[PDB]
Amino acid sequence: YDTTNPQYNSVSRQVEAGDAVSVVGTASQTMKPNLFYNKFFCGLGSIPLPKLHSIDSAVATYEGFSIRVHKYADGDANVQKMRFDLLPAYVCFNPHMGGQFFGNP
Amino acid sequence: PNNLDSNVSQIVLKKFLPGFMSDLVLAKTVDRQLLAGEINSSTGDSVSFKRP
Amino acid sequence: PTSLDVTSMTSWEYNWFGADVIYIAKYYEVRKESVDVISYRHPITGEIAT
Image (cartoon, rainbow over all chains, first blue to last red):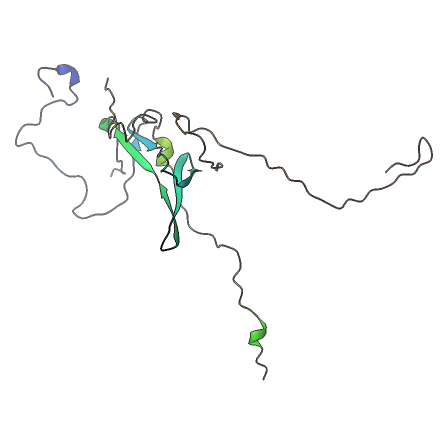
């Protein structure tokens, strides 16, 4: 609620001191929340990781997600090992386009 | 009595019993085009977008 | 659902935006099999025909 830039208002009035609030739910209830949102609420991306210096590697695919697998070994101990990695990243475009919905009484 | 249990061998078959699995819903619905191929760890740790 | 083959070959210095590609492959095999040949030996208009 900006009094000098009325273009960007999104609420009827300012929140003054002494305004009463409430918290939706129960004191210690636990539940599995339902979700509803728009297409441009949140974004998802998987960064592709590069190879290491002289280590055998390959790329796998599983529902449009690429995972890099590295194979190497320890010399003196004579042990072989593998590893799988993935690097994600998240954004939140506009919080006013999503939330949680529950059955009303 | 015949003690002929050394005439047979215990065999473990080369078959795997089915396991449990989950499903992917939230991954498909969210948009991936805007953030795809936009940030690199070498370049930095953050990319930005412009609001209307 | 769709499950695609994995090669981890491309995206090597190339920007990717379309996750709407599924990789399917055709498999060729050659086998040695037993087949029974029937020799129709009708004399009219040539006889030896297997």
